[PDB]
Image (cartoon, coloured by chain):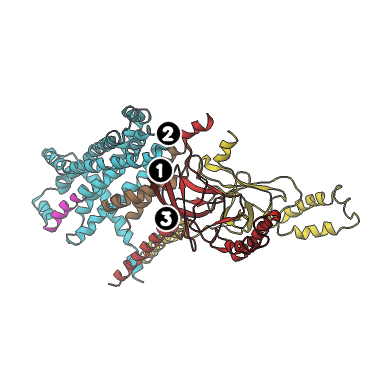
Chain colours: A cyan, B yellow, C red, D brown
């Protein structure tokens, strides 16, 4: 009987744990960072973003090569090979480049923000910092969080740019599609202010919930190097539940 | 309070098990298979593109499904065994006598009661129990034909009513029938 | 230990269901198979855009598939190999005797009686045993042609019945074939 | 197990949402079930299952 009250009340220290992470989050941003903050901030970009760059090109090149490969072969049977450029653009831009960009980012850097802070918890790296006297919420959290916010919309555009230019390589170089009908298929149907701008506003709140969880779940974890992996999934699990859970409100507010 | 919190979380999660089966209904493997139905059948000569569980419509609104298709090999006849609804396809208690006396307005009419035995009342009496159950909303003269939905891929069944005085029973066979045609009708008359 | 015997035993529960979903509610191999199904063959001219494992129909009922599509450079043609059904295409014994003496009614068809032999049993008794030899519902001179399920869709075999009084055997070759017709041919249809 | 159901529920809700609205304009809402199946089964359920 005691398991269902052990599985009971498990939300409560989780919702009290989530309520702590909100109280942490105001305490990081509502203070002006000092000198020396920008120097670590650049190195976090060097750590998070520049290291993440080599991945999303290859998965960017891939998905366009697939999506323009298979829908056309069923679409060519009626009258349409000129709407190939529209369907590749409008599903990458308003649907996948918000979503699938984060799940590769929560993969690489959604972990390396936790285990780098799961580093300083096991050898009391964290505790020594407080004891000498800094505050890691200013020192090792705030330059980590501010790189995580910036670097994801700096990638998901980069992602979808090779995403579209990838599907051109299968079309005009192997399927022999007309170049003019390819691009002017897009230019009539893809406005800038409603698709590419609103593909960014999706990618900001997909960057905040992905990186704030990955900072907090590495900070307030017990230093046990078994539970450093159970804390690792709760980065990925709570990211992927919420990066997918908040596409469906963001799709509805923009259109529909 | 311990107890409070516990019980709360309990019921809360429990729900997730409760909505699971309502989510399991939409899987199609359990739940929502038609209630209070019955069965008719008809005979065709062309059933082009017709698959099981296709739609059956009265005038543009669906009333059942098509379940068993066969071909009779001895005179080359198709035969579909389909199930209608029993809530949107039948009269209730009040609507029976409200149309049975409209049926008796046709049964004991000036054209029919005068030509038959005009000193009896048994034909007005036997028609009520016979039309009590084993009755439909489909007229005794009504043709079923395979229409073409999707205008490029489909063939839901269309039941066209009209005319008549009496109706058909709950298990009978619709005899006025019209099998579908093809693009080869669309070309041959055109050529 | 005790939770682990539960939480992976419940995992193989769900994986078996989601394989059952794909096999028995999605893909074609959900039982698609008739009884003693025999094979025949036929030759065509246009087999343009016809995949193997297509449908075969007689009155729009799925009586079989297409197995293999080969060319023969010996005579510049294409020879289709396909397997029909054995129950929906062969008469049962009751249906056999229904048409066998009706073929004897066809044989002794007035002049048909005193035209081959009214003084011998070669045109009288052999057609009785020729009625039984692996008989088909496909008559002696029906014609097969490639239809398309709607004027924008796939390709599949339909068989036009009618005509003639004798039949064919299992493994024969249907005569009178005509292939598919397309946009490059409908110009030749009008002018 | 708890992850791939939610991302499983998601991608089908999207892929049958947007291609149809362009496909409905000619004659085809019946090929909706094909395009959802044949891109999940031979293309994405190998690939996107591993990356989660």
Which secondary structure lies at badge 3?
A: loop
The image shows residue B134 at horizontal and vertical percentages of 70, 59
User: Residue B148 occupies which quadrant of the picture?
Assistant: top right
Where A147 sits versus A82, above or below? Answer: below
Residue at 65% over, 52% down: B89
Q: Which residue is mark 1?
A: C76
Q: Is residue A211 visible?
A: no
Query: Tag 3: Cα neighbours inside 10 Å, few (<14), some, or many (≥20)?
Result: few
Looking at the magenta stretch, what is its main secondary structure?
helix
Which secondary structure lies at badge 2?
A: loop
Q: Nearer the viewer, mark 1 or mark 3?
A: 1
Q: Are marks 1 and 3 on the same chain?
A: yes
C-alpha distance separating marks 1 and 3: 36 Å
Residues in magenta, as a range: A110-123
User: Residue A250 occupies which quadrant of the picture?
Assistant: top left
Q: Which residue is mark 2?
A: A79
């Amino acid at each position: 009987m005691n398991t269902i009250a052990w599985l009971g009340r498990l939300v409560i220290e989780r919702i009290r744990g989530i309520g702590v992470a909100a109280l942490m989050l105001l305490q990081i941003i509502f203070s002006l960072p000092s000198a020396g903050g920008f120097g670590r901030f650049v190195y976090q970009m060097h750590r998070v973003g520049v290291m993440s760059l080599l991945i999303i090109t290859v998965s960017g090149l891939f998905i366009g090569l697939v999506l323009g490969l298979q829908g056309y072969s069923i679409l060519v049977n009626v009258g349409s090979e000129s709407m190939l450029g529209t369907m590749v653009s409008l599903t990458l831009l308003r649907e996948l480049a918000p979503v699938v960009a984060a799940l590769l980012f929560a993969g690489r850097a959604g972990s390396a923000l936790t285990a780098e802070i799961g580093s300083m918890k096991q050898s009391e790296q964290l505790a020594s910092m407080e004891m000498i006297g800094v505050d890691p919420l200013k020192q090792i959290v705030s330059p980590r969080l501010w790189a995580g916010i910036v670097s994801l919309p700096m990638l998901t555009v980069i992602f979808a740019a090779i995403g579209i230019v990838g599907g051109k390589l299968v079309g005009v170089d192997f399927l022999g599609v007309d170049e003019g009908s390819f691009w002017s298929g897009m230019q009539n149907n893809v406005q800038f202010g409603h698709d590419v701008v609103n593909g960014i506003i999706k990618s900001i709140v997909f960057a905040l919930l992905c990186t704030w969880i990955a900072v907090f779940q590495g900070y307030a974890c017990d230093p046990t190097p078994e539970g450093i992996a159970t804390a690792m999934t709760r980065t990925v699990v709570y990211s992927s539940l919420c990066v997918l859970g908040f596409d469906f409100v963001l799709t509805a507010v923009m259109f529909g | 309070s311990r107890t409070s919190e516990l019980a709360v979380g309990i019921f809360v999660i429990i729900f997730g098990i409760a909505l699971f089966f309502l989510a399991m209904k939409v899987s199609g493997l359990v739940g929502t298979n038609l209630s209070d139905g019955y069965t008719m059948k008809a005979q065709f000569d062309n059933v082009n593109g017709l698959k099981p569980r296709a739609k059956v419509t009265m005038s543009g609104v669906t009333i059942g499904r098509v379940d068993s298709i066969t071909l009779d090999p001895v005179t080359r006849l198709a035969t579909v065994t389909f199930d209608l609804d029993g809530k949107l396809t039948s009269f209730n208690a009040e609507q029976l006598k409200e149309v049975q006396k409209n049926a008796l307005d046709e049964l004991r009419y000036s054209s029919d009661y005068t030509q038959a035995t005009p000193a009896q009342q048994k034909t007005m009496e036997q028609q009520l129990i016979s039309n009590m159950n084993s009755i439909t909303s489909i007229d005794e003269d009504a043709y079923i034909m395979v229409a073409t939905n999707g205008l490029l891929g489909e063939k839901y069944l269309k039941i066209v009513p009209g005319g008549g005085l009496n109706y058909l029973k709950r298990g009978d066979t619709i005899s006025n029938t019209q099998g579908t045609m093809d693009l080869e009708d669309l070309i041959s008359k055109f050529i």
